[PDB]
């Protein structure tokens, strides 16, 4: 049995294209004590990958590329897991995972499709959940603005905010995504940053200011949102995708003093800090899904070999929904 | 009787007749006036936290003074007050945001510094927003200034390691030898990153920012897990003809799961009594020190005013009227 794997060959400069990865065929090993062996089925493609090439150590050169995934346990030398289980874990960009199941959890394939355990019922879902609710602390009637709003995190964030009684405004790229936000996910409004002036969009959509800004994007979008925040607003720093491929320095928010004028808070978060609360998060999210109160879209791309090419879709805005790679 | 005033024209010294207080009003002989950096920010156009001084109107100044006549249920003749008394001999109007100060518990001018606005800013911004704990490392910008020098001393009292950033070898010496800061970084002569690397081994848990600009952006690179950055001001940016700099390292808040939060001292006006009571005991026991640089004569105003961005004020700048 062969285990195909993408390895990190070189730390990339800007956008990471080919020759950044090395496609390698190594023989399938066997798990040691405390380890499990997993047949990888669906891989999560995440903007955080660029950073992996910080809050977590980077990928070692010559190591398998880091990747969250869902897979079938073939064998287990670990009390927590048994052969036949389906697991969410750091499975890597390869056919098969062998190692310590640290922070792995079982998923039930009969209750939801596997790729869902990478979105709304996975990491991106939890990010939206804990970031919005614990850090954003939205309340009934508050104006909630979300960047990267048609994405996996933003789309779930927008909807939970809607369920909390918030007026929800999405900032997204292109007419199709902005239409999706309003007609499908139930956002109160949308701003197409690619086609309309963002400031005028915000003035239109948030005339009395913004109480909660969920930032997935950073850059000029963040800086413009800053001129419009309300007294005691919360800015959740979830990501800065517009900056991840910078050869140049990060674009700092020149309107940051709005946080002073408005006595507002800007706070960062990392989803793994909430691991102890995952079951309660996953449980409540699941009931939202079942009740039709929240919708999750996955964008599945087939074939492990397409990894380098498919990854770039996140940075070109080419993904429509949570990007998943079928192995 | 005459009320000498400075009203916003660069200014204008105009003698005016002393009027008389109506209902809801008090009459106050102004004794000491607060010269604050915020005086500049008040003169701008864009929506600040409080509306600008109107063209032609008496220049805003916080001050301490004696009530001569009260037509207000909360104030009595002979009370001493703190309030927006303005750049003038006498205040007449509603005591919007005034409070009584006990002249027995402290020197009158101290009710403009540690027991006044700058002291309460340090008090509430550090403790409510920074929430420093025993053994945490607390870095203060403008640490020699009126807010920073108090914030750093309260930090010391809470059991923190306290590191100050200040201009000049003299001021840095003062923080360590006189105020009891654990370390000091001379931003004017020394590299800041190296200074911070040196003075803050375990990273930075609380940053009390009075300055913004490059200092903030450098501090961001060494904040710790779950750090708190208190935005109190951005003095290095107030005299900019062009755009505020902006922290390029702000994503440190993400990597470190840290919080950056602004505050305005008057939001805590209702809690001033407990804050002032505690601050008074610290001063009285000699645990916390307050410096005021007092210049005599209202007439010296425009000259005295030219000090707060220079760095010439040693202590809280106060004008005796
Ligand atoms: N802090 C944590 O714990 C944590 C965990 C997971 C993810 N994240 C972060 O959350 C954010 C969203 O991730 P996701 O999984 O939901 O990915 P996603 O939003 O589903 O996909 C990426 C989206 O980013 C937008 N985008 C890319 N470049 C942009 C640019 N230059 N300007 C504006 N928009 C741009 C594109 O949307 P448009 O086509 O609409 O422009 C693209 O569809 C990322 O910043 C990620 O790093 C944080
Ligand atoms: N948010 C609120 O409620 C509130 C209340 C009061 C004050 N503030 C703000 O907090 C700040 C402190 O006010 P303060 O009364 O304590 O004034 P201050 O510190 O007594 O006077 C100015 C001090 O700022 C420092 N400074 C000036 N320009 C600088 C620069 N370019 N780089 C580095 N340091 C510089 C100087 O320190 P060195 O001489 O050592 O360089 C100087 O001592 C101001 O920005 C003020 O507007 C906010």
Image (cartoon, coloured by chain):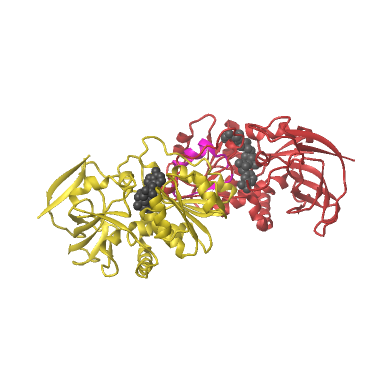
Chain colours: A red, B yellow
Picture coordinates of residue A4, whole percent (x, y): 83, 38
The quadrant in which the C terminus of chain B is found is bottom left
In the image, A292 versus A40, the foreground residue is A40
Residue B174, image quadrant: bottom left
Indicate whether B29 appears above or below B168.
below
- Left-right relation of A105 to B188: right
The quadrant in which the N terminus of chain B is found is bottom left
Residue at x 72% of width, y 47% of height: A117
- Left-right relation of B213 to A245: left
- Left-right relation of B138 to A216: left
Picture coordinates of residue B176, whole percent (x, y): 43, 58
Q: Which residues are magenta?
A: A216-238
Picture coordinates of residue A63, whole percent (x, y): 77, 41
Residue B162: tell me if it is visible: yes
Residue A305, image quadrant: top right
In the image, A128 versus B17, the foreground residue is B17
Residue at x 12% of width, y 49% of height: B16
């Amino acid at each position: 049995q062969i285990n195909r794997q993408y390895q990190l060959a070189q730390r990339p400069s800007g956008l990471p294209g080919r020759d950044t990865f090395s496609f390698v065929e190594t023989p399938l090993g066997e798990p040691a004590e405390g380890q499990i062996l997993v047949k990888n089925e669906y891989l999560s493609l995440d903007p955080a990958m660029r950073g992996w090439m910080s809050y977590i150590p980077p990928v070692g050169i010559g190591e398998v590329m880091r990747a969250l995934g869902v897979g079938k346990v073939l064998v287990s030398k670990h009390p927590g897991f048994q052969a036949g289980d389906y697991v969410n874990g750091a499975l890597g960009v390869q056919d098969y995972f062998i190692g310590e199941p640290k922070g792995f959890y079982k998923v039930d394939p009969s209750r939801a499709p596997l790729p869902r355990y990478l979105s709304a019922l996975g990491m991106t879902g939890m990010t939206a959940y804990f970031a919005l609710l614990d850090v954003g602390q939205p309340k009934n009637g508050e104006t909630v603005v979300i960047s990267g709003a048609a994405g996996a995190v933003g789309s779930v964030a927008g909807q939970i905010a809607r369920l909390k009684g918030c007026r929800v405004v999405g900032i997204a790229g292109g007419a199709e995504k902005c239409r999706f936000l309003v007609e499908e996910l139930g956002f109160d409004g949308a701003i197409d940053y690619k086609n309309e002036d963002l400031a005028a969009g915000l003035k239109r959509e948030c005339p009395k200011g913004i109480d909660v800004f969920f930032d997935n994007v950073g850059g000029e979008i963040l800086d413009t949102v800053l001129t419009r925040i309300a007294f005691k607003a919360r800015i959740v720093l979830c990501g800065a995708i517009s900056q991840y491929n910078n050869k140049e320095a990060v674009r700092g928010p020149a309107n940051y003093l709005s946080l002073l004028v408005n006595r507002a808070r800007m706070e960062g978060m990392v989803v793994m800090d909430y691991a102890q609360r995952f079951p309660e998060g996953l449980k409540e999210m699941a009931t939202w899904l079942a009740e039709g109160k929240l919708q999750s879209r996955e964008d599945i791309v087939e074939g492990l070999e397409t990894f380098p090419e498919t990854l770039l879709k996140l940075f070109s805005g080419e993904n429509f929904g949570k990007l998943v790679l079928k192995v």
